[PDB]
Length: 265
Length: 265
Ligand SMILES: Nc1ncnc2c1ncn2[C@@H]1O[C@H](CSCC[C@H](N)C(=O)O)[C@@H](O)[C@H]1O
Image 1 (tube, rainbow over the protein chains, first blue to last red):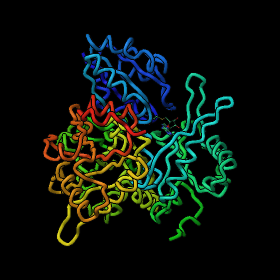
Image 2: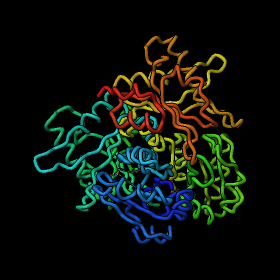
Image 3: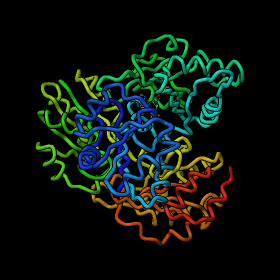
Image 4: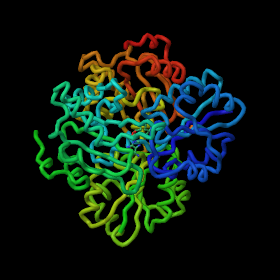
């Protein structure tokens, strides 16, 4: 009678930790959700084969609205697992589900997995230098989210990097590309004119982290906004003040313009 | 011709990903470094038995200085694995190793694993709300670092949470406890008088992240400074402004005082 939150990792079924796999193999029921992120290198069938269990996929509504009516009842009499892409508690609201579990008298444990939040280290940007993070959300009809613009501005004033999670509408198979994110940001810039995100802004794009051959690119918006970074998922980063070692890596590994090596002090 | 940077994860030998383990098992040579961080819940022997390959441990100098003299020459003609605690490249110096590999004409790939940066999500605090991060280091001789104090100040001023890594005597396997960190912070507060860290400051302690039985506690410094949080490692977090779900999680899961529920959003 327990509930395991288990992360599946960044890209494919092998991104789960050994700990996660062995525990999942011992569970009576295995649930999962694939709406918080996209695992571009695998399929539900491959994950099921690896774990050797049939997986019950839940929709956002199943979870947010009925987690305690679908999953918790079973966890009271069986060992249950709830799988999620990346790390289960990063850039999701699944942490709140641990409260529902507790109040239902169900013990829960968390098994971590690689997350895009730390995988950004592969960009060469100092991870301790990132400030507040935000999500570039899809406009919805007349509704046009812009709060993430203010996040970049706040971090930039402090010389900190900004990690921009890109939106995803799994049920509509909508996965925001770094290009779309840049386009939206430029539109927000035209509205706010804060001089935060322009054609001359240096950005970093990381696509399909977790794969052996992810796309890591750095350059000015005007040059990357029309570049093909490959299939999603994508994350966008707006660096703050670059240190020489960060610039060196972006140039050597991400093909950034050599001119960024000449940092401004 | 290939060099694999493989992360070992948070706590023990099972924290490596399936992908990382399977790749390591296929390598001709396997190196490991335990000077940037440590695997508190395991030993070199257990990691070695899990992979089934002999593992050669490298010192700080072996890597920082002679990486190209020890590892790269072998990577030129063989498949080589370089194991590191946590997630590869989260450690700042590791990024340049990829450049050295490139310079030496050796291909390198990164196999991610869980890192504290993403694992702190288990504290129930929103990952988006974390600001700049810092490390609390042992004062030694005529060196008493205090910059981490200013990081907290700047983050808190913006309502952001502050992730504080605690110092470690890598070679000696000696860890700074959350208790010692609180002591130091209270001392820095005395010589800073910024009202940033006091007996009434709410803090969160995360012990042994990655283990199946981590300790997660939250409360005011005055009440937690002398509490036993169990074996290391310990991570300290100074929350900024909480929203109600973060507060509820801390109360329900971390045993925080009900007082914190009067959030200030
Ligand atoms: N492997 C990956 N590569 C690049 N971006 C990724 C990624 N994983 C997810 N993302 C980005 O982040 C969004 C999901 S946010 C939730 C992520 C997950 N909990 C984790 O720990 O990784 C996606 O819409 C995408 O923009």
